[PDB]
Length: 273
Image 1 (spheres, rainbow, N blue to C red):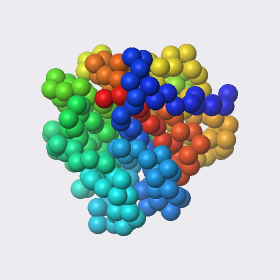
Image 2: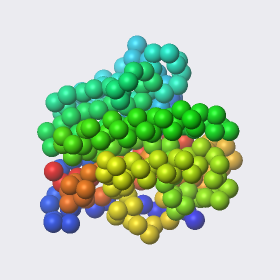
Image 3: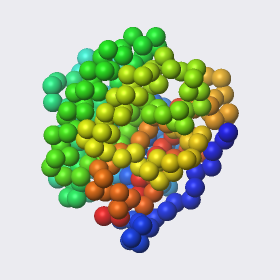
Image 4: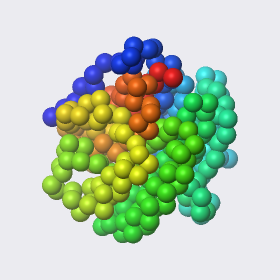
């Protein structure tokens, strides 16, 4: 019940070489993640685009080591006004996006950045957690609806890549304890339904599951507590979702289980654009 990520497939089914590498990572504390060597791993992974969620760091406190990534020199940050110490996302890109926007239209929690590139639009998101004891599930349900709507009036323009921490394991294969977590944040019925609606309405494909429909034990998050990470007791909360039009560009969708620094691990997408 431990998992070994298959090797990197850097060739599309029509046989073209991957031209774009996107890495997404919930860092659960950007400053702590940086002190735990996250930027060293990123530099090794060398993505063209790096998305980060749950930064928990205001723009004024962004450590200057981030400017020491000249291969990801264009950096955009979204932080909440009200909340201090919670939320926050970032998008770092080798090339400048044609346009960058923040939020989902009715603002400000610092959860979503939208970067328009030449061939596609990239959304990164830190979806609100339903909370211990489902306290914020009502907020989460309305956010899902708003987000779904926002994304619809977006993929109507160009193909869409949505990455980040969606805070839900879609199906049972997506977590280690399906039956014990049916009323816990991330596996409620309302939350699994919302993910399904996300996929139906936009529409989007789950990159990893498209490529690995039968693969179990593939998680991107483990609670710090107990030793869940060491025992692979975890959840797949972090996704790359794509418009159908992009499936022929899809070379691979990775889970970087070995990379430390957070209670989530990175995920990496390869596309042949």
